[PDB]
Length: 311
Image 1: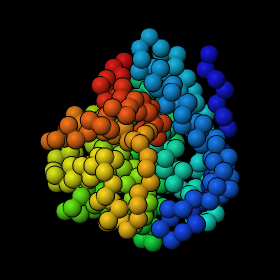
Image 2: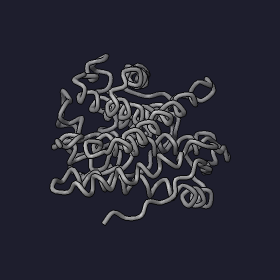
Image 3: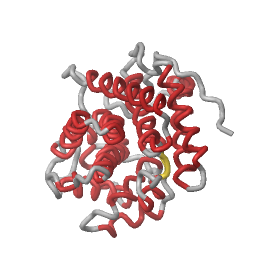
Image 4: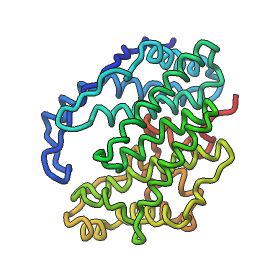
C-alpha cells in the first residue's frame, strides 16, 4: 500500500527567519511561515527515506518500489527545477540542496528495483538538480559554508547511482573544500561566527563531509585519507563541545545553546568506526538512534548494514 505522492512543483519559495547579523536569533513567525511553505519538501524527504528504510529491512521490495514511485512522480513533474525565491535570504536554494540530497540518497539505495523508464526519468531529473545546485555556487558572493558541503550530498549520490565520473569529481571538490577549510585548531571559521549556534553549525557541517566519504567507499575510494587528521580535529571539537562547550563559548564569543545530539549528528555512527580515537564519540553514540531523511534515513542502521542493501 504505497501512499499517494504529494505534488512536485517546479518552484520553491522558502522564507528566511534569522534577525541578527550572525544569523543565530530566530523569528517565530518567520520560521512558522517557512515550515508551512516547505512542508511538501519536508514531507517528500521523510517518506522516501522511510520507504528506503523498510526496503533495507528486508522482505519488503514493495516499499522499495514505493520510494521509486515517489521519485518518478517528482521527476516527471520537473519538481524543484523552476523558480527559486529569495525572501530575506536564499532559503529556497538551501531547501533545494537538502531535498535533492534526500531524493538522491533514497534513489541510490533503492535503484536496484527501478524500471527502465524509472531509471531514465529519475536519473535525468537527478542530473539537472545536480547541475542547478552547482551553478548556484558560481556567484562568488554566495559564501561556501555547510550549504556548500550539503550541496555535494545530492551530487555524490547521483554520481554513485549513475556511475557519472564527472559528477564524482565535482562532489570530490566539494568534499576537499570542506576538509581544506578546517583550521589547525579544528575550527571552521564560517561556522564559528554563529554565536550561540557555533557548535550546532560545526556539527551540521561535519555530517555532509562524513556522508560523502562514506559514499566514496561504495566506489572503492577512501576519501578519509585526504589530509588525514583534519576531519578528526573537527569531529573531536564537536564531541568535546557536547560534553563541555567552553571552547565554542570562547572562540565564538557567546554561550552555546544547550542541546543534545540529534538527527544529522548521526554522522557519528559512521565516523566512530573510522576515528583514531573512537571512544571520544561514545556519549554521542549513546544518544542514538539517529535518523535524518537528508542523509538517507536511519544512520545507525546504515552504519551497521551498509548504505545500499544488497539486492
